[PDB]
Amino acid sequence: GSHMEAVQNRIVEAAERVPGVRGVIHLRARYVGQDIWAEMIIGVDPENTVEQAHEICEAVQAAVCGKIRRIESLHVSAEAREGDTTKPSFS
Amino acid sequence: GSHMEAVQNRIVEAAERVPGVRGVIHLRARYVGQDIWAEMIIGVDPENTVEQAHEICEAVQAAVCGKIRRIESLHVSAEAREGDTTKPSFS
Ligand SMILES: [Zn+2]
Ligand SMILES: [Zn+2]
Ligand SMILES: [Zn+2]
Ligand SMILES: [Zn+2]
Ligand SMILES: [Zn+2]
Ligand SMILES: [Zn+2]
């Protein structure tokens, strides 16, 4: 599992460094050839507007794609979160 | 394709009847046995707070799950949308 574990760890670490991110709630990734396709859901402040949340999604996309060049496709979106124990995370 | 086409059509129709939904942007579903597992992203007003958006997600989950009894698992979340031509939809 190490290849995908390493990729997922790097994605989570990069996303969590972006201000406004409240953990990574969901993450799925696959190799296609030597490239990676991934979809992720970050936690965000519930009081953000959806358009403010999306600015966080865009910042996460930039950070993750910039740091991990094998990623060819990344979809980021958000759900509400807080030390939250009511949703999954990689925290 | 008819089995899954029919399911997807029913999911989209049910979701679009919920006030606050601005189209279905993304939808993936699979059978597991005779049951359905699905994940979907709805469009919502960008000026909603994320917590207001989530009330729409919950209303969509109730509507879709209530109308289509074979669905055993449904994850609904949201992205910003408006006659929007900048994101995909089933519109
Ligand atoms: Zn977003
Ligand atoms: Zn964007
Ligand atoms: Zn979720
Ligand atoms: Zn939601
Ligand atoms: Zn909920
Ligand atoms: Zn999307």
Image: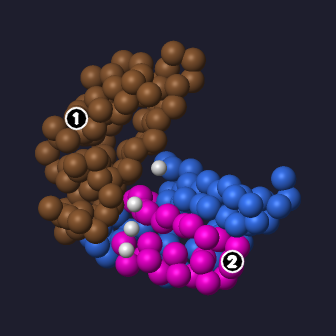
Chain colours: A brown, B blue
Picture quarter containing residue A63?
top left
Q: Position of residue B90 (x, y in %)?
A: 64, 59
Q: The disc labelled 1 sits on which kind of residue?
A: Glu
Picture residue at 50% right of the left edge, 60% below the top: B41
Report whether A20 appears left or right of A76: left
Q: Which mark is residue B68?
A: 2
Q: The disc labelled 2 sits on which kind of residue?
A: Ile
Q: Position of residue A21 (x, y in %)?
A: 20, 49
The residue wearing badge 1 is A13
Image height of A68 relative to A15, above or below? above
Q: Which residues are magenta?
A: B54-81
- Quarter containing ligand 5? bottom left
Image height of B73 relative to B63, above or below? above
Q: Which mark is residue B56?
A: none
Q: Residue furthest top?
A: A34
Q: Give whichever of B88, A24 is nearer the camera.
A: A24
- Tag 1 secondary structure: helix
Picture residue at 62% right of the left edge, 54% below the top: B28
Q: Read off the chain for label 2.
A: B
Give the CA separation, mark 2 to mark 1: 39 Å
Q: Read off the chain for label 1.
A: A
Q: Position of residue B91 (x, y in %)?
A: 64, 62
Picture residue at 23% right of the left edge, 58% below the top: A44
